[PDB]
Protein backbone atom coordinates (compact mmCIF):
# COMPACT_ATOMS: atom_id res chain seq x y z
CA UNK A 1 0.00 0.00 0.00
CA UNK A 2 3.14 2.18 0.33
CA UNK A 3 4.97 3.01 3.55
CA UNK A 4 7.95 4.71 5.20
CA UNK A 5 11.13 3.54 6.91
CA UNK A 6 11.67 5.40 10.20
CA UNK A 7 15.15 5.84 11.74
CA UNK A 8 15.07 7.32 15.26
CA UNK A 9 18.20 8.55 17.04
CA UNK A 10 21.71 7.19 16.60
CA UNK A 11 25.30 7.92 17.69
CA UNK A 12 27.76 10.00 15.63
CA UNK A 13 30.51 10.53 18.22
CA UNK A 14 27.67 11.49 20.54
CA UNK A 15 23.95 10.61 20.94
CA UNK A 16 21.85 12.05 18.10
CA UNK A 17 18.26 13.29 18.20
CA UNK A 18 17.08 12.95 14.62
CA UNK A 19 13.87 11.21 13.68
CA UNK A 20 14.11 10.63 9.89
CA UNK A 21 11.90 8.87 7.34
CA UNK A 22 12.80 7.23 4.03
CA UNK A 23 10.47 6.51 1.09
CA UNK A 24 11.86 3.97 -1.48
CA UNK A 25 8.90 4.65 -3.79
CA UNK A 26 10.73 7.89 -4.60
CA UNK A 27 14.15 7.35 -2.96
CA UNK A 28 13.67 10.52 -0.85
CA UNK A 29 14.15 11.41 2.82
CA UNK A 30 11.91 13.26 5.30
CA UNK A 31 12.70 15.13 8.53
CA UNK A 32 10.28 14.63 11.46
CA UNK A 33 10.03 15.75 15.11
CA UNK A 34 13.31 15.08 16.91
CA UNK A 35 13.71 12.84 19.96
CA UNK A 36 12.78 14.57 23.22
CA UNK A 37 16.24 13.52 24.58
CA UNK A 38 19.26 12.18 22.59
CA UNK A 39 19.63 8.39 22.94
CA UNK A 40 22.00 5.98 21.17
CA UNK A 41 21.78 2.21 20.92
CA UNK A 42 18.04 1.98 21.45
CA UNK A 43 15.55 -0.10 19.45
CA UNK A 44 12.48 0.85 17.40
CA UNK A 45 9.17 -0.89 16.62
CA UNK A 46 5.65 -0.04 15.44
CA UNK A 47 2.51 -1.00 17.36
CA UNK A 48 -0.93 -0.02 16.07
CA UNK A 49 0.68 2.26 13.47
CA UNK A 50 2.50 4.19 16.23
CA UNK A 51 6.30 4.05 16.54
CA UNK A 52 8.10 3.22 19.83
CA UNK A 53 11.74 3.80 20.79
CA UNK A 54 13.05 1.84 23.73
CA UNK A 55 16.00 2.19 26.08
CA UNK A 56 19.50 2.95 24.85
CA UNK A 57 22.04 5.40 26.30
CA UNK A 58 22.68 9.14 26.17
CA UNK A 59 26.38 9.61 25.53
CA UNK A 60 27.83 13.13 25.51
CA UNK A 61 31.09 14.81 26.75
CA UNK A 62 28.64 16.25 29.28
CA UNK A 63 28.42 12.87 31.06
CA UNK A 64 26.62 9.70 29.98
CA UNK A 65 23.46 8.09 31.32
CA UNK A 66 21.57 4.86 30.57
CA UNK A 67 17.85 5.19 29.77
CA UNK A 68 14.83 3.18 30.75
CA UNK A 69 12.75 5.43 28.53
CA UNK A 70 9.80 4.26 26.43
CA UNK A 71 8.73 7.07 24.10
CA UNK A 72 5.96 6.69 21.48
CA UNK A 73 5.87 8.77 18.25
CA UNK A 74 2.72 9.41 16.17
CA UNK A 75 3.34 10.10 12.42
CA UNK A 76 -0.19 11.58 12.20
CA UNK A 77 0.59 14.40 14.64
CA UNK A 78 4.39 14.46 14.44
CA UNK A 79 4.60 14.30 18.24
CA UNK A 80 6.57 12.17 20.74
CA UNK A 81 5.05 11.17 24.10
CA UNK A 82 6.72 9.49 27.10
CA UNK A 83 5.10 6.17 27.99
CA UNK A 84 5.54 4.15 31.22
CA UNK A 85 9.32 3.47 31.52
CA UNK A 86 10.80 -0.03 31.86
CA UNK A 87 11.84 -1.57 35.19
CA UNK A 88 15.56 -1.12 34.55
CA UNK A 89 17.72 0.85 32.06
CA UNK A 90 18.85 -1.14 29.01
CA UNK A 91 21.67 0.06 26.74
CA UNK A 92 22.21 -1.93 23.51
CA UNK A 93 18.78 -3.50 24.03
CA UNK A 94 16.85 -5.66 21.56
CA UNK A 95 13.08 -5.71 21.13
CA UNK A 96 10.39 -7.94 19.66
CA UNK A 97 6.64 -7.54 19.18
CA UNK A 98 4.24 -10.44 19.82
CA UNK A 99 0.45 -10.22 19.66
CA UNK A 100 0.56 -6.43 20.11
CA UNK A 101 3.11 -6.59 22.95
CA UNK A 102 6.67 -5.23 23.28
CA UNK A 103 9.35 -7.60 24.49
CA UNK A 104 12.57 -5.93 25.67
CA UNK A 105 15.60 -8.16 26.15
CA UNK A 106 19.01 -7.89 27.80
CA UNK A 107 21.23 -4.86 27.19
CA UNK A 108 23.52 -3.00 29.63
CA UNK A 109 23.16 -0.75 32.69
CA UNK A 110 26.19 0.45 34.62
CA UNK A 111 28.46 -2.59 34.39
CA UNK A 112 25.50 -4.93 35.06
CA UNK A 113 24.90 -7.01 31.94
CA UNK A 114 21.15 -7.69 31.95
CA UNK A 115 19.58 -11.07 31.15
CA UNK A 116 16.02 -10.21 32.16
CA UNK A 117 13.06 -9.72 29.82
CA UNK A 118 9.98 -7.51 30.12
CA UNK A 119 6.69 -7.15 28.23
CA UNK A 120 4.90 -3.81 27.78
CA UNK A 121 1.17 -4.11 27.27
CA UNK A 122 0.29 -0.96 25.22
CA UNK A 123 -3.42 -1.26 25.98
CA UNK A 124 -2.66 -0.68 29.69
CA UNK A 125 0.68 1.21 29.55
CA UNK A 126 2.24 -1.36 31.85
CA UNK A 127 5.54 -3.16 32.08
CA UNK A 128 5.17 -6.82 33.15
CA UNK A 129 8.42 -8.74 33.82
CA UNK A 130 8.85 -12.12 32.08
CA UNK A 131 11.14 -15.19 32.13
CA UNK A 132 14.88 -14.25 32.01
CA UNK A 133 17.07 -15.74 29.26
CA UNK A 134 19.71 -18.45 29.67
CA UNK A 135 22.59 -16.08 28.85
CA UNK A 136 23.07 -12.42 29.74
CA UNK A 137 23.05 -10.55 26.41
CA UNK A 138 23.89 -6.95 25.49
CA UNK A 139 23.97 -5.80 21.87
CA UNK A 140 21.58 -8.63 20.97
CA UNK A 141 19.50 -9.00 17.81
CA UNK A 142 15.89 -10.19 18.24
CA UNK A 143 13.37 -11.52 15.72
CA UNK A 144 9.77 -12.64 16.12
CA UNK A 145 8.78 -15.76 14.19
CA UNK A 146 5.73 -18.04 14.50
CA UNK A 147 4.73 -16.24 17.68
CA UNK A 148 8.16 -17.13 19.15
CA UNK A 149 11.09 -14.77 19.94
CA UNK A 150 14.71 -15.30 18.87
CA UNK A 151 17.56 -13.74 20.89
CA UNK A 152 20.72 -14.00 18.79
CA UNK A 153 24.44 -13.23 19.27
CA UNK A 154 25.26 -10.52 21.82
CA UNK A 155 27.80 -9.98 24.60
CA UNK A 156 27.52 -11.44 28.12
CA UNK A 157 30.05 -8.99 29.55
CA UNK A 158 33.04 -11.32 29.72
CA UNK A 159 33.18 -12.66 26.12
CA UNK A 160 31.37 -12.13 22.78
CA UNK A 161 28.59 -14.68 22.19
CA UNK A 162 27.76 -16.77 19.14
CA UNK A 163 24.77 -18.40 20.86
CA UNK A 164 21.01 -18.10 20.27
CA UNK A 165 17.92 -18.76 22.41
CA UNK A 166 14.19 -19.15 21.74
CA UNK A 167 11.37 -17.90 23.98
CA UNK A 168 8.00 -19.65 24.02
CA UNK A 169 5.43 -16.95 25.05
CA UNK A 170 2.56 -19.42 25.64
CA UNK A 171 4.82 -21.41 28.01
CA UNK A 172 7.09 -18.59 29.29
CA UNK A 173 10.36 -20.54 29.04
CA UNK A 174 13.69 -20.36 27.23
CA UNK A 175 15.75 -22.88 25.26
CA UNK A 176 19.13 -22.66 23.55
CA UNK A 177 19.16 -23.27 19.76
CA UNK A 178 21.80 -24.01 17.07
CA UNK A 179 24.73 -21.62 17.70
CA UNK A 180 25.89 -19.40 14.82
CA UNK A 181 28.85 -19.97 12.50
CA UNK A 182 30.45 -16.71 13.64
CA UNK A 183 30.68 -14.71 16.87
CA UNK A 184 28.40 -11.67 16.41
CA UNK A 185 27.72 -8.92 18.98
CA UNK A 186 25.55 -6.05 17.77
CA UNK A 187 24.62 -7.59 14.43
CA UNK A 188 21.38 -6.87 12.56
CA UNK A 189 18.59 -9.41 13.08
CA UNK A 190 15.21 -9.91 11.38
CA UNK A 191 12.87 -12.37 9.62
CA UNK A 192 12.42 -13.05 5.90
CA UNK A 193 9.77 -15.70 5.11
CA UNK A 194 11.00 -18.53 7.33
CA UNK A 195 14.57 -17.49 8.02
CA UNK A 196 16.42 -15.54 10.73
CA UNK A 197 18.99 -13.27 9.07
CA UNK A 198 22.01 -12.03 11.03
CA UNK A 199 24.25 -9.48 9.30
CA UNK A 200 27.40 -7.80 10.58
CA UNK A 201 28.21 -7.19 14.25
CA UNK A 202 31.47 -7.45 16.18
CA UNK A 203 33.41 -10.60 17.01
CA UNK A 204 36.27 -9.30 19.17
CA UNK A 205 39.03 -8.61 16.64
CA UNK A 206 37.23 -7.08 13.63
CA UNK A 207 33.96 -5.73 12.26
CA UNK A 208 31.98 -8.25 10.21
CA UNK A 209 30.44 -8.06 6.73
CA UNK A 210 29.33 -11.71 6.58
CA UNK A 211 25.64 -12.67 6.75
CA UNK A 212 23.93 -15.98 7.61
CA UNK A 213 20.33 -17.15 8.02
CA UNK A 214 18.58 -19.81 10.08
CA UNK A 215 15.67 -21.97 8.91
CA UNK A 216 13.53 -23.43 11.71
CA UNK A 217 12.75 -26.45 9.54
CA UNK A 218 16.44 -27.23 8.97
CA UNK A 219 17.78 -25.97 12.34
CA UNK A 220 20.99 -24.79 10.62
CA UNK A 221 22.96 -21.58 9.99
CA UNK A 222 23.91 -21.13 6.31
CA UNK A 223 26.25 -18.36 5.09
CA UNK A 224 24.73 -15.93 2.53
CA UNK A 225 26.29 -13.28 0.26
CA UNK A 226 28.21 -10.63 2.30
CA UNK A 227 27.42 -6.90 2.47
CA UNK A 228 29.63 -4.40 0.64
CA UNK A 229 30.59 -2.61 3.88
CA UNK A 230 31.64 -4.10 7.22
CA UNK A 231 29.38 -2.75 9.98
CA UNK A 232 28.68 -3.14 13.70
CA UNK A 233 25.59 -1.90 15.59
CA UNK A 234 23.45 -1.08 12.56
CA UNK A 235 19.78 -0.51 11.84
CA UNK A 236 17.97 -3.32 10.01
CA UNK A 237 14.49 -3.82 8.66
CA UNK A 238 12.36 -5.33 5.89
CA UNK A 239 9.98 -3.78 3.34
CA UNK A 240 8.39 -5.48 0.29
CA UNK A 241 10.66 -8.53 0.45
CA UNK A 242 14.06 -6.84 0.94
CA UNK A 243 16.53 -6.30 3.79
CA UNK A 244 17.59 -2.69 4.38
CA UNK A 245 20.61 -2.07 6.61
CA UNK A 246 21.10 1.50 7.89
CA UNK A 247 24.50 2.84 8.91
CA UNK A 248 26.89 1.35 11.49
CA UNK A 249 30.66 1.53 12.17
CA UNK A 250 33.34 0.04 9.90
CA UNK A 251 36.23 0.07 12.40
CA UNK A 252 37.10 3.58 11.23
CA UNK A 253 34.12 5.58 9.98
CA UNK A 254 30.42 5.70 10.76
CA UNK A 255 28.66 4.70 7.54
CA UNK A 256 25.77 6.61 5.96
CA UNK A 257 25.45 3.75 3.44
CA UNK A 258 22.12 1.98 3.25
CA UNK A 259 22.42 -1.42 1.55
CA UNK A 260 19.53 -3.46 0.15
CA UNK A 261 19.27 -7.25 -0.20
CA UNK A 262 17.00 -8.97 -2.73
CA UNK A 263 16.68 -12.65 -1.65
CA UNK A 264 15.54 -13.58 -5.16
CA UNK A 265 18.92 -12.58 -6.64
CA UNK A 266 20.98 -12.95 -3.44
CA UNK A 267 22.78 -9.68 -4.20
CA UNK A 268 23.49 -6.57 -2.09
CA UNK A 269 23.15 -3.05 -3.54
CA UNK A 270 23.56 0.42 -2.00
CA UNK A 271 20.21 2.21 -2.33
CA UNK A 272 20.94 5.60 -0.67
CA UNK A 273 23.01 7.51 1.88
CA UNK A 274 21.64 8.95 5.12
CA UNK A 275 21.67 12.66 6.03
CA UNK A 276 24.65 12.00 8.35
CA UNK A 277 26.91 9.06 9.25
CA UNK A 278 25.68 7.29 12.40
CA UNK A 279 25.45 4.03 14.37
CA UNK A 280 23.26 2.59 17.13
CA UNK A 281 20.04 3.73 15.46
CA UNK A 282 16.66 1.97 15.97
CA UNK A 283 14.42 1.44 12.91
CA UNK A 284 10.85 0.49 11.85
CA UNK A 285 8.27 0.68 9.01
CA UNK A 286 4.75 2.21 8.79
CA UNK B 1 57.53 37.16 39.56
CA UNK B 2 56.25 36.43 36.02
CA UNK B 3 53.33 34.01 35.98
CA UNK B 4 51.58 31.97 33.27
CA UNK B 5 48.25 30.14 33.01
CA UNK B 6 48.73 26.63 31.60
CA UNK B 7 46.12 24.59 29.77
CA UNK B 8 47.13 20.95 29.23
CA UNK B 9 45.12 18.94 26.71
CA UNK B 10 41.34 18.79 26.50
CA UNK B 11 38.84 17.15 24.13
CA UNK B 12 37.31 18.42 20.87
CA UNK B 13 37.04 15.54 18.36
CA UNK B 14 39.56 13.34 20.14
CA UNK B 15 42.03 13.73 23.04
CA UNK B 16 44.53 16.52 22.33
CA UNK B 17 48.16 16.84 23.38
CA UNK B 18 48.24 20.64 23.38
CA UNK B 19 50.26 22.24 26.17
CA UNK B 20 49.49 25.97 25.99
CA UNK B 21 50.27 29.01 28.14
CA UNK B 22 48.27 32.22 28.47
CA UNK B 23 50.09 35.35 29.64
CA UNK B 24 47.70 38.09 30.92
CA UNK B 25 50.62 40.53 31.20
CA UNK B 26 50.36 40.78 27.42
CA UNK B 27 47.13 38.90 26.59
CA UNK B 28 49.25 36.45 24.55
CA UNK B 29 49.38 32.68 24.00
CA UNK B 30 52.48 30.45 24.08
CA UNK B 31 52.89 26.99 22.49
CA UNK B 32 54.88 24.39 24.48
CA UNK B 33 55.93 20.71 24.36
CA UNK B 34 52.97 18.41 23.61
CA UNK B 35 51.65 15.90 26.12
CA UNK B 36 53.36 12.51 25.89
CA UNK B 37 49.97 10.83 25.38
CA UNK B 38 46.71 12.68 24.48
CA UNK B 39 44.48 12.91 27.57
CA UNK B 40 41.17 14.54 28.47
CA UNK B 41 39.25 15.07 31.71
CA UNK B 42 42.56 15.23 33.60
CA UNK B 43 43.70 17.74 36.22
CA UNK B 44 46.72 20.03 36.49
CA UNK B 45 48.63 21.38 39.48
CA UNK B 46 52.03 22.88 40.23
CA UNK B 47 54.35 21.54 42.91
CA UNK B 48 57.70 23.24 43.52
CA UNK B 49 57.34 25.18 40.25
CA UNK B 50 56.88 21.94 38.28
CA UNK B 51 53.53 21.17 36.63
CA UNK B 52 51.77 17.80 37.03
CA UNK B 53 49.03 16.38 34.76
CA UNK B 54 47.06 13.64 36.40
CA UNK B 55 44.77 10.90 35.18
CA UNK B 56 42.03 11.57 32.64
CA UNK B 57 41.18 9.55 29.52
CA UNK B 58 42.48 9.10 25.99
CA UNK B 59 39.48 9.09 23.67
CA UNK B 60 39.79 8.36 19.95
CA UNK B 61 38.10 6.12 17.30
CA UNK B 62 40.84 3.45 17.82
CA UNK B 63 39.36 2.79 21.27
CA UNK B 64 38.92 4.69 24.56
CA UNK B 65 41.41 4.09 27.37
CA UNK B 66 41.63 5.51 30.90
CA UNK B 67 44.97 6.76 32.22
CA UNK B 68 46.58 6.29 35.58
CA UNK B 69 49.34 8.53 34.30
CA UNK B 70 51.31 11.07 36.30
CA UNK B 71 53.50 13.11 33.94
CA UNK B 72 55.50 16.10 35.26
CA UNK B 73 56.36 19.10 33.03
CA UNK B 74 59.31 21.44 33.63
CA UNK B 75 59.00 24.88 31.94
CA UNK B 76 62.77 25.32 32.29
CA UNK B 77 63.54 22.46 29.90
CA UNK B 78 60.13 22.41 28.16
CA UNK B 79 60.21 18.67 28.84
CA UNK B 80 57.64 16.18 30.12
CA UNK B 81 58.74 13.23 32.21
CA UNK B 82 56.61 10.25 33.26
CA UNK B 83 56.37 10.07 37.04
CA UNK B 84 55.20 7.08 39.11
CA UNK B 85 51.63 6.25 37.95
CA UNK B 86 48.72 6.08 40.41
CA UNK B 87 47.29 2.82 41.76
CA UNK B 88 44.19 2.96 39.55
CA UNK B 89 43.02 4.94 36.47
CA UNK B 90 40.84 7.99 37.17
CA UNK B 91 38.86 9.71 34.41
CA UNK B 92 37.12 12.95 35.43
CA UNK B 93 39.48 13.17 38.42
CA UNK B 94 40.09 16.19 40.62
CA UNK B 95 43.42 16.97 42.27
CA UNK B 96 44.42 19.03 45.30
CA UNK B 97 47.84 19.94 46.72
CA UNK B 98 48.47 20.00 50.48
CA UNK B 99 51.86 20.76 52.04
CA UNK B 100 53.65 20.01 48.79
CA UNK B 101 51.73 16.73 48.23
CA UNK B 102 49.23 15.69 45.52
CA UNK B 103 45.77 14.39 46.37
CA UNK B 104 43.90 12.59 43.58
CA UNK B 105 40.20 12.07 44.26
CA UNK B 106 37.39 9.97 42.76
CA UNK B 107 36.89 9.86 39.02
CA UNK B 108 35.94 6.94 36.79
CA UNK B 109 37.51 3.79 35.39
CA UNK B 110 35.26 1.84 33.09
CA UNK B 111 32.01 1.44 35.05
CA UNK B 112 33.80 1.63 38.41
CA UNK B 113 32.96 4.99 39.99
CA UNK B 114 35.94 5.51 42.33
CA UNK B 115 35.76 7.10 45.77
CA UNK B 116 39.30 6.30 46.83
CA UNK B 117 41.87 9.05 47.43
CA UNK B 118 45.64 8.82 47.05
CA UNK B 119 48.58 11.09 47.89
CA UNK B 120 51.75 11.36 45.83
CA UNK B 121 54.90 12.42 47.65
CA UNK B 122 57.08 14.04 44.91
CA UNK B 123 60.08 13.82 47.28
CA UNK B 124 59.96 10.00 46.92
CA UNK B 125 58.01 9.55 43.63
CA UNK B 126 55.54 7.45 45.64
CA UNK B 127 51.81 6.92 45.65
CA UNK B 128 50.11 6.28 49.01
CA UNK B 129 46.37 5.49 49.25
CA UNK B 130 44.52 7.49 51.93
CA UNK B 131 41.06 7.54 53.58
CA UNK B 132 38.30 7.20 50.90
CA UNK B 133 35.38 9.65 50.64
CA UNK B 134 31.81 9.14 51.88
CA UNK B 135 30.28 9.23 48.38
CA UNK B 136 31.67 7.89 45.12
CA UNK B 137 32.38 10.92 42.91
CA UNK B 138 33.40 11.31 39.28
CA UNK B 139 33.66 14.71 37.59
CA UNK B 140 34.39 16.26 40.98
CA UNK B 141 35.95 19.65 41.68
CA UNK B 142 38.53 19.96 44.47
CA UNK B 143 39.55 22.96 46.56
CA UNK B 144 42.39 23.19 49.08
CA UNK B 145 41.72 25.68 51.89
CA UNK B 146 43.02 25.92 55.48
CA UNK B 147 45.17 22.85 54.71
CA UNK B 148 41.92 20.91 54.21
CA UNK B 149 40.46 19.44 51.01
CA UNK B 150 36.94 20.06 49.68
CA UNK B 151 35.46 17.51 47.26
CA UNK B 152 32.50 19.22 45.60
CA UNK B 153 29.65 18.15 43.30
CA UNK B 154 30.33 15.21 41.00
CA UNK B 155 28.47 12.05 39.91
CA UNK B 156 28.13 8.79 41.88
CA UNK B 157 26.92 6.81 38.87
CA UNK B 158 23.19 6.81 39.59
CA UNK B 159 22.43 10.46 40.35
CA UNK B 160 24.23 13.80 39.84
CA UNK B 161 25.49 15.11 43.20
CA UNK B 162 25.03 18.52 44.78
CA UNK B 163 26.94 17.46 47.90
CA UNK B 164 30.46 18.10 49.21
CA UNK B 165 32.80 16.53 51.75
CA UNK B 166 35.85 17.76 53.68
CA UNK B 167 39.04 15.81 54.35
CA UNK B 168 41.10 16.49 57.46
CA UNK B 169 44.72 15.53 56.50
CA UNK B 170 46.14 15.57 60.05
CA UNK B 171 43.31 13.22 61.15
CA UNK B 172 42.79 11.30 57.87
CA UNK B 173 38.97 11.27 57.95
CA UNK B 174 36.03 12.71 56.00
CA UNK B 175 32.91 14.70 56.91
CA UNK B 176 30.03 15.94 54.76
CA UNK B 177 29.43 19.69 54.38
CA UNK B 178 26.31 21.74 53.54
CA UNK B 179 24.98 20.84 50.11
CA UNK B 180 24.87 23.37 47.25
CA UNK B 181 21.75 25.10 45.91
CA UNK B 182 22.30 23.49 42.51
CA UNK B 183 23.26 20.03 41.28
CA UNK B 184 26.71 20.30 39.64
CA UNK B 185 28.76 17.52 38.00
CA UNK B 186 31.99 18.66 36.33
CA UNK B 187 31.80 22.31 37.41
CA UNK B 188 34.80 24.57 38.01
CA UNK B 189 35.97 24.57 41.62
CA UNK B 190 38.53 26.83 43.37
CA UNK B 191 39.35 28.92 46.48
CA UNK B 192 39.52 32.75 46.44
CA UNK B 193 39.86 34.74 49.69
CA UNK B 194 38.13 32.08 51.81
CA UNK B 195 35.26 31.41 49.44
CA UNK B 196 34.73 28.10 47.62
CA UNK B 197 33.52 28.91 44.10
CA UNK B 198 31.59 26.45 41.94
CA UNK B 199 30.82 27.62 38.39
CA UNK B 200 28.95 25.72 35.69
CA UNK B 201 28.88 21.93 35.36
CA UNK B 202 26.00 19.60 34.51
CA UNK B 203 22.85 18.91 36.55
CA UNK B 204 21.03 16.26 34.49
CA UNK B 205 18.75 18.32 32.23
CA UNK B 206 20.87 21.34 31.25
CA UNK B 207 24.35 22.84 31.16
CA UNK B 208 24.76 25.47 33.88
CA UNK B 209 25.88 29.10 33.83
CA UNK B 210 25.07 29.82 37.50
CA UNK B 211 27.85 30.30 40.06
CA UNK B 212 27.74 30.03 43.86
CA UNK B 213 30.35 30.33 46.61
CA UNK B 214 30.78 29.03 50.16
CA UNK B 215 32.19 30.80 53.22
CA UNK B 216 33.75 28.35 55.69
CA UNK B 217 32.92 30.63 58.60
CA UNK B 218 29.26 30.99 57.66
CA UNK B 219 28.68 27.51 56.16
CA UNK B 220 26.28 28.83 53.49
CA UNK B 221 26.10 28.62 49.68
CA UNK B 222 25.11 31.93 48.07
CA UNK B 223 24.41 32.52 44.39
CA UNK B 224 26.53 35.07 42.49
CA UNK B 225 26.17 36.70 39.07
CA UNK B 226 26.24 34.09 36.24
CA UNK B 227 28.80 33.58 33.45
CA UNK B 228 28.25 34.83 29.88
CA UNK B 229 28.28 31.28 28.47
CA UNK B 230 26.80 28.05 29.89
CA UNK B 231 29.63 25.53 30.25
CA UNK B 232 30.25 22.04 31.64
CA UNK B 233 33.66 20.44 32.21
CA UNK B 234 35.76 23.60 32.00
CA UNK B 235 39.22 24.62 33.17
CA UNK B 236 39.33 26.93 36.19
CA UNK B 237 42.03 28.87 37.94
CA UNK B 238 43.01 32.13 39.61
CA UNK B 239 45.55 34.79 38.78
CA UNK B 240 46.01 37.97 40.84
CA UNK B 241 42.56 37.87 42.45
CA UNK B 242 40.37 36.89 39.49
CA UNK B 243 38.70 33.67 38.33
CA UNK B 244 39.60 32.56 34.80
CA UNK B 245 37.37 29.91 33.20
CA UNK B 246 38.76 28.12 30.12
CA UNK B 247 36.54 26.56 27.50
CA UNK B 248 33.86 23.95 28.18
CA UNK B 249 30.77 22.61 26.41
CA UNK B 250 27.56 24.62 25.97
CA UNK B 251 25.30 21.76 24.87
CA UNK B 252 26.17 22.53 21.24
CA UNK B 253 29.66 23.98 20.78
CA UNK B 254 32.95 23.44 22.55
CA UNK B 255 33.76 26.97 23.75
CA UNK B 256 36.97 28.89 23.08
CA UNK B 257 35.67 31.71 25.30
CA UNK B 258 37.81 32.47 28.35
CA UNK B 259 35.85 34.52 30.89
CA UNK B 260 37.22 36.52 33.79
CA UNK B 261 35.54 37.28 37.10
CA UNK B 262 36.43 40.31 39.20
CA UNK B 263 35.09 39.65 42.74
CA UNK B 264 35.19 43.39 43.47
CA UNK B 265 32.55 44.10 40.82
CA UNK B 266 30.95 40.65 40.69
CA UNK B 267 30.85 40.73 36.88
CA UNK B 268 32.09 38.38 34.17
CA UNK B 269 33.99 39.55 31.07
CA UNK B 270 35.56 37.65 28.15
CA UNK B 271 39.33 38.21 28.23
CA UNK B 272 40.41 36.19 25.15
CA UNK B 273 39.60 33.27 22.89
CA UNK B 274 41.53 30.03 22.81
CA UNK B 275 43.40 28.75 19.77
CA UNK B 276 40.86 25.88 19.55
CA UNK B 277 37.52 24.98 21.13
CA UNK B 278 37.86 22.29 23.81
CA UNK B 279 36.43 20.71 26.96
CA UNK B 280 37.72 18.48 29.77
CA UNK B 281 40.95 20.48 30.01
CA UNK B 282 43.12 20.68 33.15
CA UNK B 283 44.68 24.00 34.20
CA UNK B 284 47.38 25.46 36.46
CA UNK B 285 49.35 28.66 37.19
CA UNK B 286 53.14 29.18 37.51
Image: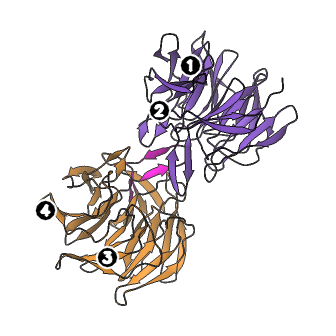
Chain colours: A orange, B purple
Q: Is residue B25 left or right of residue B275?
A: right
What's the CA distance linking mark 2 and mark 4?
52 Å
Q: Which residue is mark 3?
A: A212
Tell me what residue is drawn at x 57 percent, y 35 percent. B186
Q: Residue furthest front?
A: B124
Question: Marks 4 and 2: in contact by CB < 8 Å?
Answer: no
Tell me what residue is drawn at x 73 percent, y 43 percent. B33
Q: Which residue is mark 4?
A: A170
Q: Residues within 10 Å of mark 4 (few under 14, many from 20)?
A: few
Q: Which residue is mark 1?
A: B149
Residue A48 seen in the figure: yes
Nearer-N-terminus badge (1/2) = 2
Judging depth in this view, the residue of B159 and B128 nearest the camera is B128
Q: Nearer the viewer, mark 1 or mark 2?
A: 2
Nearer-N-terminus badge (3/4) = 4
Which picture quadrant has residue A245?
Answer: bottom left
Chain of the residue displaying label 3: A
Give how far across and how far down residue B250 sits, in percent: 64, 44
What's the CA distance linking mark 1 and mark 3?
58 Å
Q: Secondary structure at mark 1?
A: strand
Q: Nearer the viewer, mark 2 or mark 4?
A: 2
Q: Is residue A167 left or right of residue B68?
A: left
Residue A98 seen in the figure: no
Residue A60 painted magenta: yes
Tell me what residue is drawn at x 33 percent, y 51 percent. A157
- Identify the magenta region: A52-71
What's the CA distance linking mark 1 and mark 4?
60 Å
Do the residues indicated by labels 3 and 2 lie within the same chain of the protein? no
Amino acid sequence: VGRLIYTAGGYFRQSLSYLEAYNPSDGTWLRLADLQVPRSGLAGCVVGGLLYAVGGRNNSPDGNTDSSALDCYNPMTNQWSPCAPMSVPRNRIGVGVIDGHIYAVGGSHGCIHHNSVERYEPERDEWHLVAPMLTRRIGVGVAVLNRLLYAVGGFDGTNRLNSAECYYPERNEWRMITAMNTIRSGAGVCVLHNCIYAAGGYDGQDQLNSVERYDVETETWTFVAPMKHRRSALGITVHQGRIYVLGGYDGHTFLDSVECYDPDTDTWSEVTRMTSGRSGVGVAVT
